[PDB]
Image (tube, grey):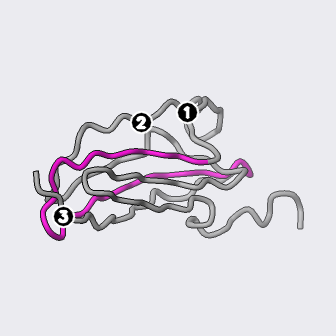
C-alpha cells in the first residue's frame, strides 16, 4: 500500500465528537486524529428551542492546502465551551463541521445533533 492509502477512515474516527452538559455549561469536544484537521470557518452551531451565549471559536493554526489556500485549522483536539442560558425540554444543538486529511482529501461537512438537557432561564 503506497503512502497514505489507508488514511480514508470513517469520519467519526478522524474527528471523534462528544459533548458534556452540566446545567448551563456545555462542553463540545473533538478528538482529532494525527494527520487530520478541522477548518475553523466550517464550524456552525445552531440552537433549537434554546438560547445560548455568543460562541467564540478559539485561535487555531494556519495551514496551506489546495482546497482553500491559506486557512485557519484545528489539530489534535478542539475544546469549545457553550453557555446555555435557556433550553426547553427536547431542545437541541445542531453542530456542523468539516475536516480534511493531510494525505490529500477532505471529508464532507458533518452534522451532529446534541440533545440538550432542559435549563430554566
Neighbourhood count class around disc 3 (C-alpha, 10 Å): few under 14, some 14–19, many 20 upward? some
Residue name at image x 40 percent, y 60 percent: 20
Q: How many marks?
A: 3
Q: Which residues are magenta?
A: 77-103
80 or 106: nearer the eye? 80
Query: Quadrant of the rendered structure where residue 67 is?
Result: top right
Confirm whether the magenta stretch covers residue 22.
Answer: no
Q: Residue at x 32, y 38 (%)?
A: 55
Q: CA distance from mark 2 to mark 3?
A: 24 Å
List x then y, in percent, for residue 101.
67, 52
Q: CA distance from mark 2 to mark 1?
A: 9 Å
Q: Is residue 80 left or right of residue 75?
A: left
Residue 63 or 56: which is nearer the viewer?
56
Residue at the extreme right: 2
- Distance Cα–Cα, label 3 vs label 1: 32 Å
The quarter of the picture where residue 60 lies is top right
> Residue placed at 61% from the left, 51% from the top?
100
Q: For mark 1, what is the residue?
A: 60
Mark 1 crowd level (few <14, some 14–19, many ≥20, 10 Å Cα): some
Query: Sequence order check: which comes first, mark 3 or mark 1?
Result: 1
Residue 105: percent from left, percent from top: 65, 53
Residues tagged 2 and 1 counted as in contact (Cβ below 8 A): yes
User: Which residue carries the number 2 mark?
Assistant: 57
Provide residue 28's location: percent of width, then percent of height: 42, 53
Q: Secondary structure at mark 2?
A: loop
Amino acid at each position: 500500500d503506497a503512502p497514505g492509502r489507508s488514511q480514508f477512515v470513517p469520519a467519526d474516527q478522524a474527528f471523534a465528537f462528544d459533548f458534556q452538559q452540566n446545567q448551563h455549561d456545555l462542553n463540545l469536544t473533538w478528538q482529532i486524529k494525527d494527520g487530520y484537521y478541522l477548518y475553523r470557518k466550517q464550524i456552525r452551531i445552531t440552537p433549537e428551542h434554546a438560547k445560548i451565549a455568543d460562541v467564540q471559536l478559539p485561535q487555531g493554526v494556519w495551514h496551506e492546502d489546495e482546497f482553500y489556500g491559506k486557512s485557519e485549522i484545528y489539530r489534535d483536539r478542539l475544546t469549545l465551551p457553550v453557555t446555555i442560558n435557556q433550553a426547553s425540554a427536547g431542545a437541541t444543538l445542531t453542530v456542523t463541521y468539516q475536516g480534511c486529511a493531510d494525505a490529500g482529501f477532505c471529508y464532507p461537512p458533518e452534522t451532529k445533533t446534541v440533545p440538550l438537557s432542559e435549563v430554566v432561564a
